[PDB]
Image (cartoon, grey):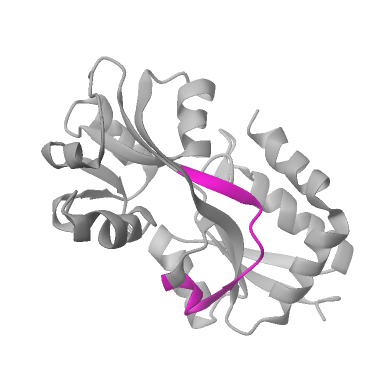
């Protein structure tokens, strides 16, 4: 159903290695390798537009875009307005400090005394609103929000922010690829899943799921792992 068809794709490429830009400004990452391989198989073409994070989710939710990707978490809230592929990665969320800032976290009752920050519109808000706030561990009203992970890290680096909420693959990019002196202090293990997003009702979601299964788990996991070092 996509043969010869051109799809409008919304991205917001500041989530390495799922989707990001090299120095030369070239778009790249797991998500692009996956979806461009799908299109090579089904003979479709991509018309890619870059948005801010909320602009990307908005475009696929309204049907302005046919497809969206940039390491997008499959959440209950988003599923009401967006159709997702099966997950290509089981994700974990870390609370991260500078290495010289010795924050020891025994349990969730200890979060309240610290500032927590992350990119506006990301799924950390859901975790807080649904899992931490009701138990009195933290309040959404106390979080610091930023445009991207880069501005979040900048406030971590200068000491303005105590803890950044950073998903595992991005954390490893900053720590191991970029060699930033940061350390996880708490891990929410396997609490999340990443998928490709499609406009509600899109048959492309179903056919992409078919393609994922044609490829098989080892091929997909191999693509994912190749990018995560």
Q: Which residue lies furthest to the top in this view?
A: 100
Task: Find the magenta span and give its range.
Answer: 77-92
Nearer the observer, 72 or 1? 72
Quarter holding the C terminus is: top right
What is the count of numbered marks?
0
What residue is shown at x 55% (from left), y 54% (from top)?
193
Image position, residue 28 (x, y; %): 64, 44
Nearer the observer, 179 or 47? 179
Is residue 102 at all visible to an observer of this figure? yes
Quarter holding the N terminus is: bottom right
Q: In this view, does 121 lie above or below 177?
A: below
- 184 lies left or right of 1: left
- 6 lies left or right of 126: right
What residue is shown at x 20% (from left), y 56% (from top)?
135
Q: Does the magenta run of residues contain 131?
A: no
Quadrant in the rendering for residue 177: top right
Image position, residue 159 (x, y; %): 18, 26
Q: Does the magenta run of residues contain 86?
A: yes
Image position, residue 210 (x, y; %): 81, 68
Q: Is residue 120 above or below residue 229?
A: below
Q: Residue furthest bottom?
A: 201
What residue is shown at x 49% (from left), y 74% (from top)?
59
Quadrant in the rendering for residue 209: bottom right
Image position, residue 147 (x, y; %): 32, 50
Is residue 39 at all visible to an observer of this figure? no
Q: Is residue 61 above or below residue 139?
A: below
- 162 lies left or right of 196: left
């Amino acid at each position: 159903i996509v043969e010869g068809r051109t799809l409008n794709v919304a991205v917001s490429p500041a989530s390495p290695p799922m989707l990001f830009k090299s120095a030369d400004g070239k778009l790249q990452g797991i998500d692009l390798e996956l979806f461009s391989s799908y299109c090579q198989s089904r003979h479709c073409k991509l018309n890619i537009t870059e948005y801010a994070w909320d602009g990307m989710l908005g475009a696929v939710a309204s049907g302005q875009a046919d497809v969206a990707f940039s390491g997008i978490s499959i959440t209950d809230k988003r599923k009401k307005v967006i159709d997702f592929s099966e997950p290509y990665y089981i994700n974990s969320f870390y609370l991260v400090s500078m290495a010289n800032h010795k924050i020891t976290l025994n349990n969730l009752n200890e979060l309240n005394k610290y500032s927590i920050g992350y990119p506006r519109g990301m799924a950390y808000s859901d975790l807080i609103k649904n899992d931490l706030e009701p138990k009195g561990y933290y309040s959404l009203s106390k979080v610091k929000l930023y445009p991207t992970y880069n501005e979040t890290m900048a406030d971590l680096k200068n000491g303005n922010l105590d803890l950044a909420f950073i998903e595992e693959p991005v954390y490893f990019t900053f720590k191991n690829k970029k060699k930033m002196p940061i350390e996880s202090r708490y891990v929410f293990k396997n609490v999340d899943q990443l998928g490709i997003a499609f406009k509600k009702g899109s048959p492309v979601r179903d056919d992409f799921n078919l393609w994922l299964k044609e490829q098989g788990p080892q091929k997909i996991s191999g693509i994912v792992d190749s990018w995560m070092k």
